[PDB]
Length: 109
Length: 110
Length: 107
Length: 110
Ligand SMILES: O=P(O)(O)O[C@H]1[C@H](O)[C@@H](O)[C@H](O)[C@H](O)[C@@H]1O
Ligand SMILES: O=P(O)(O)O[C@H]1[C@H](O)[C@@H](O)[C@H](O)[C@H](O)[C@@H]1O
Ligand SMILES: O=P(O)(O)O[C@H]1[C@H](O)[C@@H](O)[C@H](O)[C@H](O)[C@@H]1O
Image (cartoon, rainbow over all chains, first blue to last red; front, side):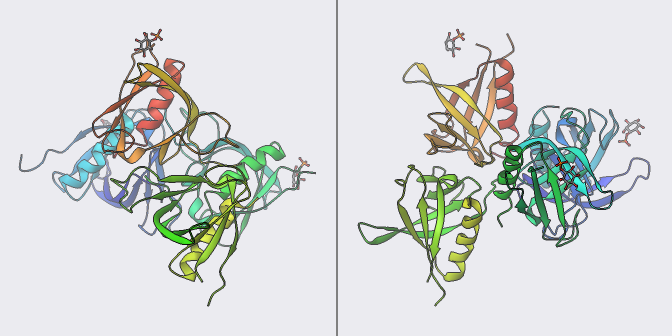
């Protein structure tokens, strides 16, 4: 229940070149993935990515100034992601993506 | 790897009821979870072994002072622990146990 | 990221004036805070923050009936040994407050 | 006897009217930076002030080389006027950074 942001995101597989969706919760410590949004019964994160090991590097530009709703989370250290690898996430709109990005930028700076 | 919203951290031993022995781990309490890590290296070892949602846990009994450094964490829902099942923790002292117990209790009242 | 246990309006009785005044309260693991209003973004300064570790809850109404008593164990906002009475809109709502408080303040 | 505290210690806050630092004992929780006159966590439990983190940010801090200061900025009118700034001083650079990084992660939406 104590969080900065939560909602669905699609995470890309580099090798498979496809996306899979999960329900994410950002807290001051972790980006957690859960299979669902039911916070009372779905209690065990699929994974918890420690923010202190991550940075957010790039994001999409708005189309007019999911195509424009991506951002990249970079691993600074070996954790869930191998050091100096990157995961790409896709939110429903540029606007929602920037909400994720702007929080993550502060948390990981 | 530098900041973390930790309310309490330290080593605890958790009794396994199948293995008949305690496993020690490095635990960190946040407002949302009691996380276990294999080690205390808060800069590098940052994938939890397990993360117990406080929203579905309670703390129920503990040792009387007079080891006397144990307490029970109970599951309200099916998670890491099956609904209605209980895990027993052992801290280094009664006093340390009560620091854990009181910090958990105030985060699991609902 | 607000960690709260419960929030809502309660009326707090004055023992001497024999009247109630209403406030918007927020129970956290550490305090029962009163605010003038429910607007969490603009009404930022607690009117008072009662430390739970200095309090117990002692009695409450039986169902017909929405009152409970918060007892000061030490001198804080309330004098040691003294009591404040709170009234919530229903027995059910009152028990929600009381049951949380009982756990938070139990020895 | 328990308290969800993420960080606590003495800080000096600069008053811009009094032209001096006032020292107080501060306790960070997930909701507030509270000031108390003393460190007596069992008896001195009415905050001097409680700064809502939802409407605070941390903005600058000292470069290593006092170098133990940081600025807390107000987003809204509260115990600081909106857009005004308070300067804190902690015993060392390292301790200042522990405060700064702990605040920063709790004030990313503010
Ligand atoms: O994020 P993943 O795990 O897909 O990491 C890849 C890096 O993304 C590439 O820069 C790099 O070129 C490598 O190919 C690497 O697999
Ligand atoms: O008195 P000590 O510190 O040896 O505590 C023991 C407990 O008494 C046992 O229940 C428990 O099963 C453990 O063996 C633990 O060692
Ligand atoms: O630690 P030192 O000796 O540098 O003391 C200074 C204070 O640190 C300043 O905040 C205050 O602004 C004064 O400039 C004062 O010089």
